[PDB]
Length: 278
Image (cartoon, rainbow, N blue to C red; front, side, top):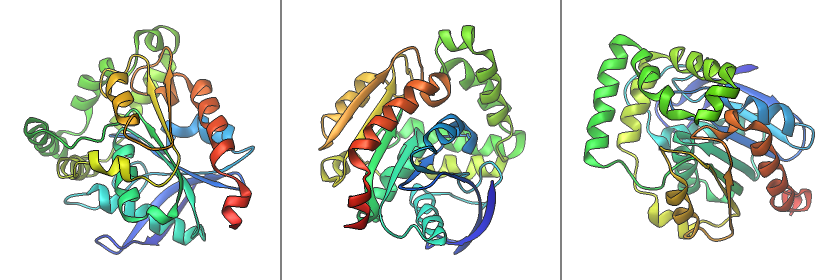
């Protein structure tokens, strides 16, 4: 992995991001969820790099990236991604993928940087904004995590994040997810919780998308359910909708091969060398 100071149009104008960059060719940036880090996309990075260039950052406040106290808006996170691509000389089109919060970041990027997208991958995410009770819950999580750290988040969320078959067949995956949550910087978690509370509604963005979009969901996702994601896909032009069997909310980790294959086959259709040149 690398760590670089990037220039970003969001406050505070410069930020140090940790990231992985593996493979050559057409760029695919994959954005983790909340409270996660770049390692949640490790299987896809390590496999897709035979055919694509896979870039996987720790977002501001997460993993090994700089923590920026206050509010980390979805827009700011998207600005940081644009700045990372600028740093790397990836100033043409990319495919951008995200899971859950990472999907919220992808929407923010599509609003602002639509001309930089060859495609979008939306996994286990939602277009609606937070309800009032969800906003209040973000504030409560922020307040507490700053002081107590993320253990309470792991305790609440682990039983909800993955399907029963993952617990039974892949206890090592459960433990990796637990460690990922437990390691998340307290103030980074807080700043992102507050940022999520204030994200806009992306419902009307969806029909306005101008690139192919892959919509992926675990069969047993209780958090961003398949019925909701299917309904989302029906409003996105040039969508492909894929339900990953025997996965909950974290298909990339629970069913890594199925997710890698779904992404690979879709990328072959949408992210071509001739499109990069012209």
